[PDB]
Image: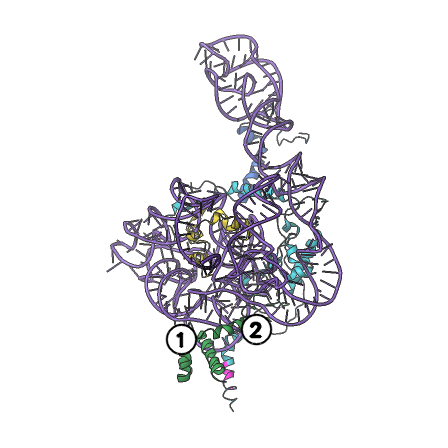
RNA sequence: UUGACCUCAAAUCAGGUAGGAAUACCCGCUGAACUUAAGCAUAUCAAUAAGCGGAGGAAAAGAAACCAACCGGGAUUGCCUUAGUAACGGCGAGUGAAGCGGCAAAAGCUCAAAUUUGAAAUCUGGCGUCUUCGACGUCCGAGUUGUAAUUUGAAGAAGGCAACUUUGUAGCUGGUCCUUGUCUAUGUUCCUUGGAACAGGACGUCAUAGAGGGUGAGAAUCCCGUGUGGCGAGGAUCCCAGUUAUUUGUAAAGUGCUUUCGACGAGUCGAGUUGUUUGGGAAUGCAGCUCUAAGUGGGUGGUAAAUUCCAUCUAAAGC
């Protein structure tokens, strides 16, 4: 909803608005029921990478923060280190425990 | 292209035409169009339609009959 | 090199410019080629118009939002609203654009009227036998022009209420500058430190 | 080739000169001075019927 | 002992295909200096000349991992504007785009990733027969480590309920478009000058033909033509029109409602660093090297980061 003036927060002209119905191409990045099943099988076959085998050793010793700094150098950016280190904790809670 | 299975079948017929002689050399392959830098965007201005083509356009004096 | 009291010019002629000169002598002759091409195409096609029927569209930016202009294609929502399929519409002389969207009820109606006006006025010949020909109209833009929407009432009441239009702009502009820090000042004092209390 | 051949002229300036030339069609002094054997002709601003 | 399969060979085996030429324009690689800065080293000339590879009558580009911040536009290409502007630069000399706006022209689409699985449905060659740029039948081979039908994000599929509107393949004549051949007006009358009238003077004729050329000197009317319109011949043929065979059909397409799903491209994206290039400035694109992902994910939003939102498209295959 616009405010009815050229300068402001909303800005500007008021119209009968809604709606565009959603396209098919907006979904794109959404999951499964093949893909999660196939990715589950392609994990037991076979193992983790060498840099990932340091991550779980680093979590047992020096927890977080150091785990991010090692992952940030090996992977691209800080935002990708968030995803990897959060995922590696879910491996320990799932596989090693219970 | 000379083999008759490729000539008759309509899905793979286009490659037999004379315009597709040495695509690899001129850079009409997947890797070729990446190396030339042909993509839609503000990042790709100096090369997009053609690097030398664009230079040849904008380094030229266009004169009409009535100036 | 310089010196009287003249303006400092900028002439970019230090490359081999004379090798890459163009003179448009062909202007007059090239016009006849296009008039010949437009005429010869109409002879081949025969009873149909040369142009596809285009929709009405509003322009972008602050500079041009106050004017309407002929777009590219009719969208999929508007073609459905009239009562026809998108695949069928392409062979009747109606342009379709799969990527344009609708977020306005005013433009939505206008183009539905434009399609209903088009479908009524055109005739269609069957595939089989008889074909009662009715000359050719060349330009679709001539028969279906673009008119500017009128948002006007020439004589009108004078309703004042001591608000001041100038004072409204100064207050509204000040809110945009300061809502960032005013949210954060409210997130301290009243929240965080006093939600602890 | 790229020397200036054609010359642009103002639209009103052409119509000024073309209008004055149509004024020059009448008036017998300017016609005889600019050639033309027009001794026989009864008057000028010469109009003919539409059978022509 | 015999026969398969997988990789690799040989033959003047059966049948095909590649080179050179020309290069005005077009697609890439490679790459100078004279010069300008009143010197000269970054810069400039120039992402230019010479050198090398590859095409066609055009080439390239092209159906958004786009432009925007509006009440939003909507593949590519070119012209007029934007602009000598925003930026770049011993911030010196000098260099220098793009969005919107008005026009010319407008056309859209295909694979991979799903099981035909109640019938590899598909295709090359051999031999035979026909109406021979092909069609029909038959015999080996290719191929299940995947050839047909079916679907491409604008969607779409599998079920249930429901009304149905559509259809197709040859040759014959005529027009149309090219290459052409032929036909279609009027003074050579009299006198002077001259080697010669095509000159000068007198009297006519034709004109939808007084363009141009030829003939012993400036010829509409002496000759070829020119103008106006006829009449043939020989190709191209699907572009149209009008016909005649056929004979496609119980198969192919479209649409209203409702439930469950909805597969989307990796030594890539992205990060660091070196060299090169751009107007692109804590780095515009390209390339080498080291590191190396993801599933509401990834890209972009022209100042480096961390934190939280929003708007926009769907890359790493192709016409």
Name above or below for residue D26 compared with residue D39: below
The x, y position of residue E171, in whole percent, is 64, 38
Q: Is residue C109 positioned above or below B58 on the image?
A: below
- Return the mark for residue C168: 2
Q: Please name the color used to draw chain C.
A: cyan
Of all chains, the one bearing label 1 is: A
Q: Position of residue E234 (x, y in %)?
A: 58, 31
Q: Which stretch appears magenta? A: C184-189
Q: Chain of mark 2?
A: C
Give the CA separation, mark 2 to mark 1. 61 Å
Q: Which chain is purple?
A: E
| Whole-percent x, y for residue E95 in the image | 38, 55
Magenta: main secondary structure equals helix
* Residue drawn at x 64%, y 50% as measured from the top left: C140
Look at chain B in the picture and name its colour: yellow
Secondary structure under tag 1 reads helix
Chain D, which colour? blue
Colour of chain A in the rendered structure image: green
Question: Which label number is shown at residue B59?
Answer: none
Tag shown at residue A51:
1
């Amino acid at each position: 909803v616009k405010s009815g003036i050229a300068v402001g927060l909303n800005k500007g002209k008021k119209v009968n608005q809604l709606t565009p119905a959603p396209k098919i191409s907006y979904r794109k990045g959404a999951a499964s029921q093949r893909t999660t099943f196939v990715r589950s099988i392609v994990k037991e076959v076979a193992s983790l990478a060498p840099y990932e085998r340091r991550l779980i050793e680093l979590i047992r010793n020096a927890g977080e923060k150091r785990a991010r700094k090692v992952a940030k150098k090996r992977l691209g950016t800080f935002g990708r280190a968030k995803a990897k280190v959060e995922e590696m904790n879910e491996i320990i809670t799932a596989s090693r425990r219970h | 292209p000379s083999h008759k299975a490729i000539r008759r079948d309509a899905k793979y017929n286009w490659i037999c035409n004379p315009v597709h002689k040495h695509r690899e050399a001129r850079g009409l392959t997947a890797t070729g169009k990446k190396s030339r830098g042909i993509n839609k965007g503000h990042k790709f201005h100096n090369t997009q339609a053609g690097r030398r083509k664009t230079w040849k356009r904008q380094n030229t004096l266009s004169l009409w009959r009535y100036r | 090199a310089i010196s009287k009291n003249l303006p400092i010019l900028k002439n970019h002629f230090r490359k081999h410019w004379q090798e890459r000169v163009k003179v448009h002598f062909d202007q007059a002759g090239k016009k006849v080629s296009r008039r010949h091409a437009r005429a010869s195409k109409a002879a081949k096609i025969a009873p149909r118009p040369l142009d596809l029927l285009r929709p009405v569209v509003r322009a972008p930016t602050v500079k041009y939002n106050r004017k309407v202009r002929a777009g590219r294609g009719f969208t999929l929502a508007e073609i459905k609203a009239a009562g026809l399929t998108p695949a069928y519409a392409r062979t009747i002389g109606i342009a379709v654009d799969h990527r344009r969207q609708n977020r306005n009820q005013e433009i939505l109606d206008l183009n539905i009227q434009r399609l209903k006006e088009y479908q009524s006025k055109i005739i269609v010949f069957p595939r089989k036998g008889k074909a009662p020909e009715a000359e050719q109209t060349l330009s679709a833009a001539a028969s279906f022009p673009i008119v500017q929407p009128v948002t006007d009432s020439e004589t009108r009441a004078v309703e004042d209420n001591g608000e001041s239009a100038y004072r409204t702009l100064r207050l509204a502009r000040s809110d945009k500058r300061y809502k960032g820090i005013r949210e954060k000042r409210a997130k301290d004092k009243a929240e965080a430190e006093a939600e602890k209390k | 080739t790229w020397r200036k051949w054609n010359v642009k002229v103002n639209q009103n300036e052409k119509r000024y000169a073309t209008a004055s030339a149509i004024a020059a069609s009448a008036v017998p002094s300017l016609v005889l001075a600019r050639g033309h054997r027009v001794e026989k002709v009864p008057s000028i601003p010469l109009v003919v019927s539409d059978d022509l």
